[PDB]
Length: 100
Image 1: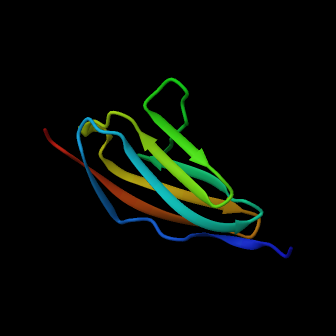
Image 2 (image 1 turned 30 degrees about the vertical axis):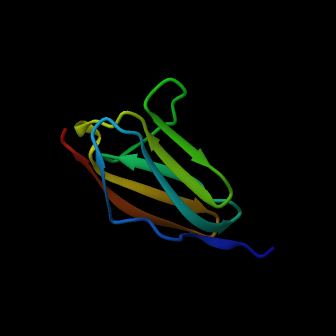
């Protein structure tokens, strides 16, 4: 086909979750060819780690950020960026971790 610039369908502005739980943030998108997905926090790319607490699952129209056993230190602004040959898009979600 002709190609389609990437577009984050929607990302929440804010999400609150209890400390100690597993956070799951799914976000739908469009783009052709499939956009490269980058999640970042503090200006730094988050890497999906088999043995860590942070995991990322990407498909052709969805990306899901997973944070296991969330801690207060995990709170903050997470940026999702999408890039392909026809353009880019980004959005930020503020993750709030609730005490106790």
